[PDB]
Amino acid sequence: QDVQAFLKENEEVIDQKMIEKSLNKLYEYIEQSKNCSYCGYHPKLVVNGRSIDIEYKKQQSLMKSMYIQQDLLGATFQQVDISDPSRLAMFQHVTDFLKSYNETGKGKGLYLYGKFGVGKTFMLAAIANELAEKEYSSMIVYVPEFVRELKNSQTLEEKLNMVKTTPVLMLDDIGAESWVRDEVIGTVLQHRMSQQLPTFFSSNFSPDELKHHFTYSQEVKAARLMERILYLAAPIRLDGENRR
Amino acid sequence: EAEQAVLGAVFLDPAALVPASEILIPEDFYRAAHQKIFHAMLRVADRGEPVDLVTVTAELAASEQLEEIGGVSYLSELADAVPTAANVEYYARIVEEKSVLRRLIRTATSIAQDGYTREDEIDVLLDEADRKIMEITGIPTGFTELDRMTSGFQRSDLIIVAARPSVGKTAFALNIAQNVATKTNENVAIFSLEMSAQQLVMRMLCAEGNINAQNLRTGKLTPEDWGKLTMAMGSLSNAGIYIDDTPSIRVSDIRAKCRRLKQESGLGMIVIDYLQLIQEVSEISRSLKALARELEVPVIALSQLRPMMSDIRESGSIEQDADIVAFLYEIIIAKQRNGPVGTVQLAFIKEYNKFVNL
Image 1: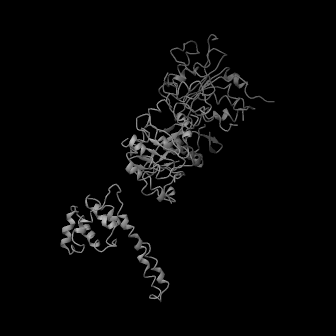
Image 2: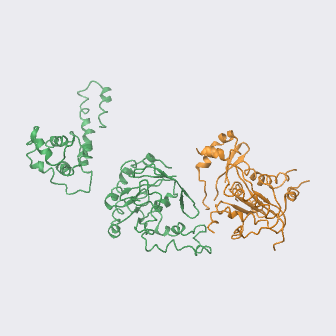
Image 3: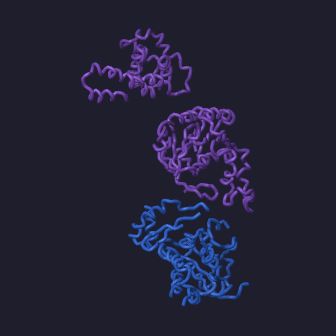
């Protein structure tokens, strides 16, 4: 019965036969502790070639945000002002889906792309409390502070297991430091498209810019990192006066 | 001197034959006056039919047997002894320990002669001559969950836990006995022999206060665990759990030490150090099963091991008089002298020493 559940859960990723081949793994996966003791790791399934392996208000509570300041993550929707195509062409993809969000059927996220300061992350931290009216283990992260300590080493076998297939991922900022990121997030964004999952984005630049800036050499490994980030959704503008 | 006494108790029950029909048969008679008496007893309770003193005495007057025993004078003195009651079985075993012998001993007399009489045979003189020889109710375990299958830990049992070497059972045998002294009332005796009195104090606070991701050994924690602590030791006084380690006190001594408290508090639980460090086990461990029955205390007289049953039932008892026996790896109570023998879904954080359910 567990196999049935898992099969259909990841049937977008698994090749029926792959499931039966990695049966031992998936069965050992469910049989062991699905939790940890730091709350130090938890088991998650990953597809490696042809085999599946196992790698390790009263609304903001059981959440587990990574590498972020403690109390900045409190934002609502009445308080969020409604302005330009920064906020009048977005509440058309946000509200069509509210109390209607499935797993076993991919959903539409968003990619907030634009300037340096206006309002990158106020439409990924506000909705993280719509993902707090129902309460998901919604992740909120600084990717400027993510390609540094995970280059380090000690512990490194499994460091991004909460940055893959969590019910929600409100990715914020990537503006610091053929890249050290093609067997990393480029295969992280692979499990966000075959185990039935959507993700959330916001950063400093834009789709056109980021493709022209990633991975350089003397190789289209710079123009494959970013359609792993232009698939589940269509990016829309952010415009308005400065906020500093 | 069993036979002089044994019948006395059997009399006034009317059910001192339930284990006694199991123990003694019409062969179990060293004596001569006694053998037909019991057959006049056994003929009765087969309807049955009813059971009392006399239903046998006028039965004996009938089918050829009354002076055979010297009148009713000794038929009276079958009764006149048993200066006791709290034994239980017990007792008829004395007669069975006058019995078992000769079913394994009277069967070796012919042979002692089957060499100068049966001269004359040899091999078949073995095939047969060796054959004969043989012949919440119900106090919870702390949980609000383990409260509806069996319930208790009621009022009297023997419990012996065996999981992988020194794990969370080490915690659990005692994490059975937590929500009883502080969070309700009943003072529970948790004595020790391995983990001393100066070894079971800092880690109950690890188990209580939202304080353990630190840890607590350094003296001073972080600016939060002192704002959130008054849970761990504040009500410890008005509770009722205290710790001892009289090196390794024997099976009679603690058995005789749980008499200070049985008068004082009533004695609620006895969480003992593994009955294996206490001083081949179907013998030594049979002095804490019955202490539960008279002292009226749940007695956690334990073990130190995978888990499997006739595997701790290996060199000793365990699958016998011993009551409920669970199996930690999820609590696999694949044995519980309790009724609903079953597994309860659980887990563990290991972060703040607090265990989980589902």
